[PDB]
Every structure is written in structure tokens, then in C-alpha cells.
Length: 373
Ligand SMILES: CC(C)(C)CCNC(=O)CCc1cc2cc(-c3ccccc3C#CCC3(NC(=O)c4ccc(F)cc4)CC3)ccc2nc1N
Image 1: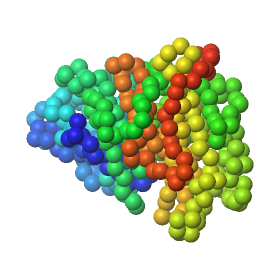
Image 2: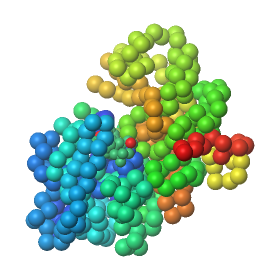
Image 3: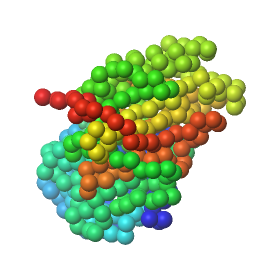
Image 4: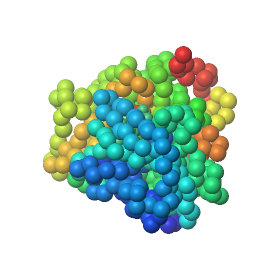
């Protein structure tokens, strides 16, 4: 898997993308890696934000499916035409597959002005594909048509440029330290998981664990922050504020609306607590924990200045890039489980160490799951 190491790039706050080729002859595009959606969709007309776009009429292997696709999101959208074509990942497995492709012809609030990606690779499951779950996602096609094993793994390493690795079809031992622990994929739609306990510097938050997963918890490379359900966010912020109270911060800092700065290299990392998320384990009544250092949740932005990268959610927990940057994450689709291990590229603390540790004894973990009617 050495050929796939370092196949991801990005810019701060703009996501991670991988190089792909589409069509015959191959058209090279940079594609955002998104575990929180399930469509393969590419700019296919000259939106001013795009470095380049897919030109479907120049591909001899493009097949028009003669069906439109429309994907609304928070008063924005992408829209276009469905087809299939041959797709490869140059720094990936040595195969080519015929996959569904959405050729985006109109959009609002989707592309980012100044980013270096032109499309999105939705790696989640068919249930959340548009227009419906009959549109087979890319990874499903990859596994069906080739001998690539049904798993991939992500090491995201944290404008300043960014990098990482997407290992397609396996695990690279060089990308983590310590042990890999697995949590079940609760259901195949999002990469849904169940958080069973939360601690701040070892202090139990002491909430009904259902609150941690209200109304779901997902692992999402398509989101920057650790996003927490409102009630949990408020409890977490209260605790982090208490821990760090020897310094004063504007109210807006805790809302992610202003920076806090310190003289070069005098950042008081010690006053910010570690956060442990306990995840449902593979065995009955067994859990494990992942521990994130403050270096994960205080995002550097151009003194050393930082933005608070924990935010409130009204649609459940989102373990975004912030969390993922601390860990090598294994999406073991074949066995309906997600693995975590400390990332070989995570940012270290002077005196404390990140961890993925277990086992713990946690009873009635099924009750931590929220039941969306
Ligand atoms: C409902 C739908 C299928 C659209 C998404 C369901 N998923 C979520 O709600 C989780 C968050 C998310 C929202 C998304 C929204 C869209 C979308 C659809 C129509 C119009 C606009 C958008 C958008 C957006 C934001 C986005 N993400 C980033 O720009 C990004 C920024 C920083 C990062 F670190 C990672 C990603 C480009 C996907 C596309 C993919 C998404 N992927 C995601 N994981």
C-alpha cells in the first residue's frame, strides 16, 4: 500500500482531496473525500470557482443515463445529469471501474472559491445517495467489479497546506501507533456509531448516554469540527471553561467566532483538558476510549492564534476532521465496523499522550442509541 501513502492533499478548512481520473482518454480531477455522503459528483460546466471540470462529451466511454439529479442542502444545491464512465485513482489500486457519475451543471453553496477540488467522492452507503438508494455508490462499484477488499482507511494529517493517506482496500501499519480498536457501524447509511461515555480530564460528563447520540453520531471527513448535540456541547464547554479559567476568553471564542492568540510558543496547552469519547466495542458490555488532546480541538489559523473547533449541532454528533486528524480510522465495511488507533501524524503535547485504550465494562450500551421513529 506504499503507493497510496500521502495520496491526500488540502488547504486548512477546505477538506482533503484525492486525485482521480474519469473517462477515455482520462480526465484528471481533484476530488473531496467525504465519508458523510454517497454520491460521486463532479463539476461538469465552467463554474468560476473551478480549476477544471469534467467534459463528458470528450469521453468515448461516457454513457448518459438520461436522468437528472438534484441535491438540496441548507438553501444551496447541486444539480446535474447522471451517467456512467470509467474511473481510476492514480495513487490507489491498479484498477478501473465503471461507476455512476453526477455531472454537476448548476450549483449554489457547494464549490469553494479558492479550493483545489472539483468534485466529491461520497464514501457512505446507498441509503443516503441521491436521487435514491438504487444509485450504486462508487466504493460499492469498486468492490463489486474488482478484487479490492471492502474496506478503506484514512489518515488525515493537519492558507497552510494539508496532507494525508487514503488506503483503499487495506490497512497500512506505518500510519498508526498502539492498538486498533473497533466500534460497530450501527447502521449502513452514514458511518453511524454509538458513544457510550464522555470524560473531560477523566471527569465523567454524567449525562444520559442517549444525549451523546441524539439523534445520531457519525464519522465524517466532510466536516471540519467535532460537532456535539446542544445539551452535550453546553456541558462540554462548561467543563473546558472551568479547566481553563485562569485565562479569560471572549464569549465569541467559545462560539468559534473569534480567535485567541498567544506570543509565539507560549500557548498554555496545559490548561486545556483532554476529552475521552468511549465508543461501543465489538464484544457484549465492552467499550473502548479515544482520547483527544487540546491540539486537536484548537485549530491553528494565521503570534500563535487558534479557533475553537468544537461546535453545537442540532443533527447529532459529528466526528469531523478535527477528531480524525488525531487517529488512523479504518472503515471496515466488510465487517460493519470502524477502527481507531492513534495516528502516526497527530500533533503531540509536551507532557500528555493521545490514546486508544480498552477494554472497559459498559452495561446497557444499546440504550445509548437514539431511535429515530
Ligand atoms: C444530505 C446530503 C446527502 C447532502 C449530505 C448528508 N451529510 C451531512 O449532512 C453531513 C455533512 C455533509 C454535508 C454535505 C453537503 C453537501 C452539499 C449538497 C448541496 C449543496 C452544498 C453542499 C455542501 C457542502 C459542504 C461540503 N464540505 C466541505 O466543503 C468541507 C469543508 C471542510 C472539511 F474539512 C471537509 C469538507 C462540500 C461538502 C454535499 C456533501 C456533504 N457531505 C457532508 N458530509
